[PDB]
Image (cartoon, rainbow over all chains, first blue to last red; front, side, top):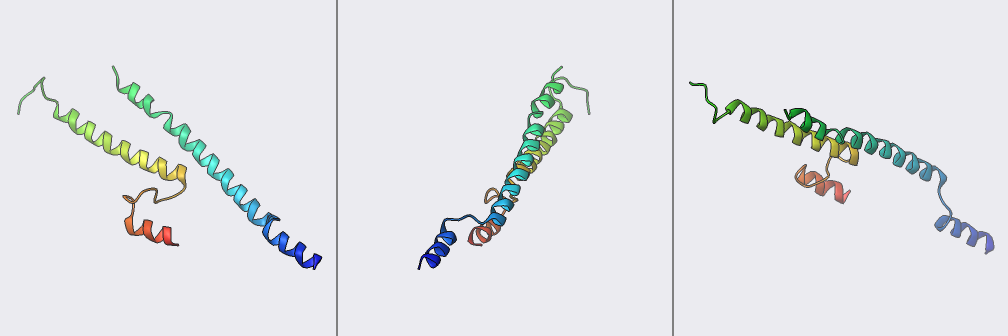
Length: 53
Length: 54
């Protein structure tokens, strides 16, 4: 009974390392993508400035 | 045809195409940062419904 209970508790509480590592990598690439997008977007008011004159 | 000071139709054309390009740029930036092609129903209504149900 203890072996089966430990197995069931692992199914519910213990983490899946493959899925979690995949999710972590996906989150990291998403963070870099948002970094690049934000860096590009921080330059539109520069285009506004170059028009003034 | 004449050379005027009060109206600048070429300026209006440039402003219109500039706003169009800016809107396209903002849409592309939103899709790139979000990672989703459909971030509102105006992108694709049936696509949004299908993606939500899936």
